[PDB]
Length: 95
Length: 95
Length: 95
Length: 95
Ligand SMILES: [K+]
Ligand SMILES: [K+]
Ligand SMILES: [K+]
Ligand SMILES: [K+]
Ligand SMILES: [K+]
Ligand SMILES: [K+]
Image (cartoon, rainbow over all chains, first blue to last red; front, side, top):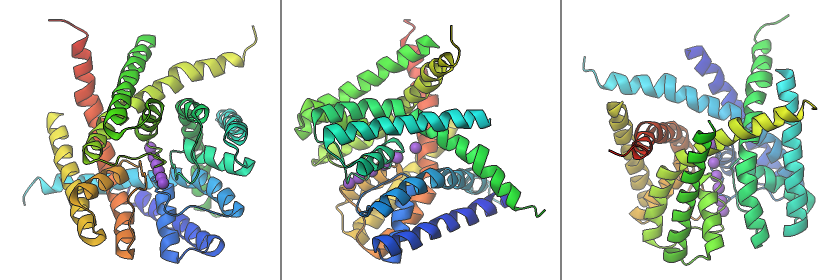
């Protein structure tokens, strides 16, 4: 379950690195903005302060969303159930 | 389970084709933009770089979201559990 | 299960009517735009072509999201599992 | 189950207070706007009427989304199943 978490964590980082490199290069974003946009996209927040302007970028974004959402949300779920929840429970019981 | 996936895949493509034809025609979008907007809508990202301007388009969008989200997210789930997950597990074991 | 669906359907309509009346009145939207915005909000798409400008509207929106998401998505789930899925299965078997 | 709800409720309030203080201070938003933006972010609506402009804000937002979504949506789920659903059922049976 901690190895579950480690693998999803690594996969999430790799997925976000892919987006960061793509949007920096093809859409011309600063790397921090490309990382931020990748996160805002795959968590489905979608502010629209950044959005792709090239056709190559729009096509990549379609594919990135379909591949990336299941991973990101799997990580979020394991984070909440396997890390946040036990730490909250631990806080209720003084030692 | 691979036939589960094939059917959801076909249904997702058909749903995205419907949106592409509608928004190209009624909202005047280029086809690639109409496909991109359909994806951004049904995955609930919603950048707002494109949004419907006609009343016909707003009404269609209401109905398209309610019909389209359950399908799209069903496909994403099967993609992640039935295709991505086994391929990740396979990568852990050299042959 | 069809009464499950009927109740969620009615509750969803009532929730969308509430939003339509509120945003028309307080935020000055045309009724069709207020309905569209309510749907775009509770399904978490969030284009931002419309957004509340008054403090009363922002406060209402906070509460409307928290009360409305669980209902809307419950309806979507029952729609997909209890109506769309059987009709798809029925299409596979000629009579 | 009512203590389940109380704990998630308190945690959600604390998470929203954190965002309110951060975005007011670092991004210069009025407190009501910072609360509204925090809610719009963690429920994944993402209108984009407000979005972070500083790099410190973008980095905080990445981390806030990953930590905050699992909590917020856990609260929404318990709200819908443990509070809204029983009250709806109660309304069906006159006393
Ligand atoms: K969104
Ligand atoms: K969303
Ligand atoms: K969601
Ligand atoms: K926007
Ligand atoms: K959005
Ligand atoms: K937006």
